[PDB]
Structure formats: C-alpha cells, structure tokens
Image 1: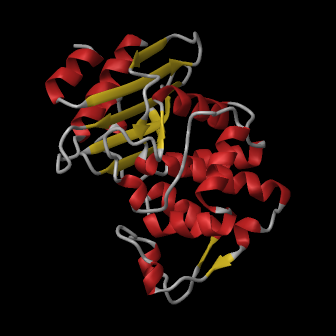
Image 2 (image 1 turned 30 degrees about the vertical axis):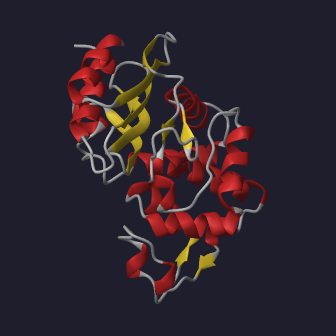
Image 3 (image 1 turned 90 degrees about the horizontal axis):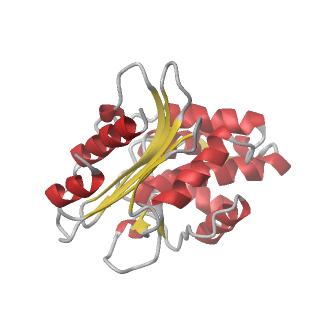
Length: 258
C-alpha cells in the first residue's frame, strides 16, 4: 500500500524521493538516508562531462583509445570498439543508455576521476553525493559504507536542476535529456510503474547486496513532470536485484502525486 509496507514485504531498505514540480508536493521514504548509488551516478558523470565541454567545446569530439585490459565487466558497447576507439560523446551515450562500465571509467580518466565528479556535484548544490571509486568497485554496496553513496533527496534535487533547471546551459541540458530518455536498460523499473503515455528519462543502477536503483524524470502527457529517485538495498551479499520493487515504488509515488 505504502513505501513502508513495500519495504516490509520485500525486505531490505527502500529510499524514495518523488517531487511534483508543479506543487512541490513530495512522496518520501528514507529520503535523507545514504544509499549506494551504483550506476545512477552515470547521470552525474554525463552532466560533469557536458559542463567541462562548456569551457572546452571540442571535448565531446575527442577520441579515446583504450585496450582489452581497460575493459571491466559489463561493457556491451565499448567491447565492440577496442580497435577504433570512441569519442567522449559516444562514451557518454554508452554509459547512460546502456550503463556501460568501461565507458564510465574512460570518461572519468579524461575529466579527473571520482574527485572530479564529486566536485561537479558540489558545484550544483549537492553537498551529499560522494564518488570515491571506479567501476566496478563502486558497486560493492557494503552495509554501513559511505563510499559511493548519496541520498534519494540529493539525487532528486540534482535531477530537478539538471533536467528542469539551469544547472547546464540549454544545449547541454537538451543533450543530457536526450541521453536519459534513451535509456535502453530500464524497462522493468520506473518505466514499468508509469502508464505507457508518460515519458521517462532515467538512469538505473545495480550492485551487490541486491542493490536495485533507478532515478529520473517523468513527463505525464497533461501534467507537469515528476522527479523520482528510488534506491533499494538488501541485507545479504548475494541477494538478487528486485526490479519489481522499483516498479511498485513508482506506482505508489505516482498515485500519491496524482
């Protein structure tokens, strides 16, 4: 019935921040607790790359050459381009739309590592987010570890100002939205919990301890958008990701904000 009820049924710890951008009403659960963000940080990474390209417009064109030993687990796009390289823009699209892990590392090598993503977060008003590690270690999702964590509220605030606000200049804002709307690997999470008429731009995350996340912006066809951040993590190290918990949380959040 409710987020608290969903959590009790699924087990684990569920964090939600949903914001109706027309009224500021929210649907919340553990919204100020830290969670391991896993691949949802790739939305921030893309934003940080886009922001660096504002003073250096050629950044998105730069070609990155990497080798077999640079590939980490789950690299479905980059593993096809070991012999050609990829541009920074192509790496952004791969990491956001397919969650490619090597693409994230290659982008962070270009822009100054975990510290550069964290500094970017601070620059848009997020004093909570911390990126400490690289792919795939940042997905360990250990109970009680603050590395590679944020709160549902901080990530919802970031999405609001990046997608619906003026944190990025308009051209870069449009590109971030295009990338997020093009997510190919999230159909069973937030996208499964909204009507097929609503449009979604989102980034999923998955990690150890059955960590299952999805953050994004929801555009209903005839009402203002809703910003939704959902984080979920479990007690046992070998727990299985639960896509359906994210879809169910999305149904509750959308109904609260109806």
